[PDB]
DNA sequence: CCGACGCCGCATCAGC
DNA sequence: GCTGATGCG
DNA sequence: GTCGG
C-alpha cells in the first residue's frame, strides 16, 4: 500500500480507456504501469523516479507529479463529472455488459440500476444473471469460505468419478486472503490431447454440483468451460452466504501443467510471461508451449512435466504461485 | 518514428 | 444449418 | 500509453 494512491489513480484511468474510450491498449498500458508501481518497494516521491520503471513513460510521469503535488488528477475529476462516462463506467460493472452494450444502453436511456431492473427484457441470459447478483458479485470471498467451497467441490467431484482431479486456482492458489471468485481446473484420464474417450465429462460434474444445490445458475457452458454461480449452504436461522461466481475449466490431462500455470495467473503475470516467451521465441497458451519458426509459425508442442519446465524454456527463474500476484 | 501489444472459450449475429 | 466476425469474460 | 530496434 506504499503507493496505493498512485496505483488507484492509474486503475481508474485504465478502466476509463477500456469502458469509455474503448482503447484496449491504453487500458493495458495503464494496467502495466499500476502493476509495476504496486510492487515497487519505496514510497514514490516524484514522476521522474517513477519514469525509471518499465511501463511508466512521460505522460504517466506527469500525471504522478500532478497527483503528488495536489492529491488529485484533473483528468479524472472531469471524467468523474461527465454523466455519459460515469453511466457507461457503472453499467460495465454488471457481468455480461461490456463497453459496447453499456454505450448502447446509455444511448437508449438505460443509465441506472433501476433502469436495468426495469428493462430486464432487453438483457441476454448472462447479463440477466449478472444483474440478479450484482450486489453479491461485488463482495470479496474470505479465504476461510474458499476453503469450505473447495471441500464441497472436491468431494462432489470424487462422488461422480474417483478419477477426476479438481484443483482450485486463481488468486486462491496464489495464497490470497480473499478472492473475487472460485476458479477450478478439472482433469479426467478419459480426455487427453489424443482422444476424448467419454462424452459429457464437464456436464456430469456440473449436473452433480447442481444436484446438491451448490451451483445455482449458469452464465455460459460448453464442452470445456463452465461459467456460473454457486453458494455455500448456511445453518439453521443463519443469514445466507452471498452468491459467488464459479469458473470451471476442463483441460486435457496430459496438458495439466500449462493449464494450471494459466489458471493460477495473475492476468498481468500471464501477460508479462507470454510476452517474454514471444521475445524468447516461444508461444504459450493454456495447452502447450511451442517454438516459433523462422516464419513466425508456432511449431509442435514441447514436452512439459512441471510448471517449472515452462519457466525453464523461456529462461525465467521459477516463481511460486504466491509470488505471481502482479 | 512506429508497429506491436497474450491467448482463447462460449454466446450472439450477419450472411449464405 | 454452417462459417466467420464480434462482444465478453 | 509505452517501448525496442
Ligand atoms: N485477462 C485474463 C484474465 C484471467 N486470466 C487467467 C489468470 C487468472 O488468475 C485466471 C482466473 O481469472 P480471474 O478473473 O478469476 O482472476 P484471479 O483469480 O487471478 O483473481 P480474482 O481473485 O479477482 O478472481 O485466469 C488470464 O490469463 N487473462
Ligand atoms: Mg478468480
Ligand atoms: Mg474466474
Ligand atoms: Na461487465
Image: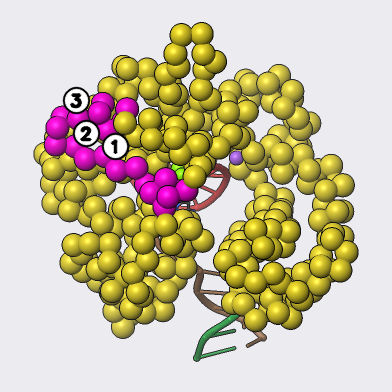
Chain colours: A yellow, B brown, C red, D green
A206 or A158: which is nearer to us? Answer: A158
> Callout 1: few (<14), some (14-19), or many (20+) C-alpha neighbours within 10 Å?
few
**Residue drawn at x 75%, y 74% as measured from the top left:** A45
| Disc 3 target residue | A159
Ligand 3's image quarter is top left
Q: Does the segment drawn in magenta span residue A172?
A: yes
Answer whether labels 1 and 2 touch (C-beta < 8 Å). Answer: yes
Determine the secondary structure under disc 1: loop
Examine the rendered structure and indicate whether residue A206 appears above or below residue A178: above
The first of marks 3 and 1 along the sequence is: 3
Check disc 3: other Cα within 10 Å, few if <14, some if 14-19, many if 20+. few
Q: Chain of mark 2?
A: A
Q: Which residues are magenta?
A: A152-176
Q: Nearer the viewer, residue A209 or A132?
A: A209
Q: Secondary structure at mark 2?
A: helix
Q: Is residue A297 above or below residue A235?
A: below
Q: Is residue A59 visible?
A: no
- The circle drawn on residue A223 is 1
Q: Earlier in the sequence, mark 1 or mark 2?
A: 2
Q: Where residue A4 appears, x then y in whole percent?
A: 69, 58
Amino acid at each position: 500500500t506504499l503507493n496505493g494512491g498512485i496505483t488507484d489513480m492509474l486503475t481508474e484511468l485504465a478502466n476509463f480507456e477500456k469502458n469509455v474510450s474503448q482503447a484496449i491498449h491504453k487500458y493495458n498500458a495503464y494496467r502495466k504501469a499500476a502493476s509495476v508501481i504496486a510492487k515497487y518497494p519505496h514510497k514514490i516521491k516524484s514522476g521522474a523516479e517513477a519514469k525509471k520503471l518499465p511501463g511508466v513513460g512521460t505522460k504517466i510521469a506527469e500525471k504522478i507529479d500532478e497527483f503528488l503535488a495536489t492529491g488529485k488528477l484533473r483528468k479524472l475529476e472531469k471524467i468523474r463529472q461527465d454523466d455519459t462516462s460515469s453511466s457507461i463506467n457503472f453499467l460495465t460493472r454488471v457481468s455480461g455488459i461490456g463497453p459496447s452494450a453499456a454505450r448502447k444502453f446509455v444511448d437508449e436511456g438505460i443509465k441506472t440500476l433501476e433502469d436495468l431492473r426495469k428493462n430486464e427484457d432487453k438483457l441476454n441470459h448472462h447479463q440477466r444473471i449478472g444483474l440478479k447478483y450484482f450486489g453479491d458479485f461485488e463482495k470479496r470471498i474470505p479465504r476461510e469460505e474458499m476453503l469450505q467451497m473447495q471441500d464441497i467441490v472436491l468431494n462432489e467431484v470424487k462422488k461422480v468419478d474417483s478419477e477426476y482431479i479438481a484443483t482450485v486456482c486463481g488468486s486462491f492458489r496464489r495464497g490470497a486472503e480473499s478472492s473475487g471468485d472460485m476458479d477450478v481446473l478439472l482433469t479426467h484420464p478419459s480426455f487427453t490431447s489424443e482422444s476424448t474417450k467419454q462424452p459429457k465429462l464437464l456436464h456430469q460434474v456440473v449436473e452433480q454440483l447442481q444436484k446438491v444445490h451448490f451451483i445455482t445458475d449458469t452464465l455460459s457452458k460448453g464442452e470445456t468451460k463452465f461459467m456460473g454461480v454457486c453458494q455455500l449452504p448456511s445453518k439453521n436461522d443463519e443469514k445466507e452466504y452471498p452468491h459467488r461466481r464459479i469458473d470451471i475449466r476442463l483441460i486435457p490431462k496430459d496438458q495439466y501443467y500449462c493449464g494450471v500455470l494459466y489458471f493460477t495467473g495473475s492476468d498481468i503475470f500471464n501477460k508479462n510471461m507470454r510476452a517474454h516467451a514471444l521475445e524468447k521465441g516461444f508461444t504459450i497458451n493454456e495447452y502447450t508451449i511451442r517454438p516459433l519458426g523462422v516464419t513466425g509459425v508456432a511449431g509442435e508442442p514441447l514436452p512439459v512435466d512441471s510448471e517449472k519446465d515452462i519457466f525453464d524454456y523461456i529462461q525465467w527463474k521459477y516463481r511460486e504461485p504466491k509470488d505471481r500476484s502482479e
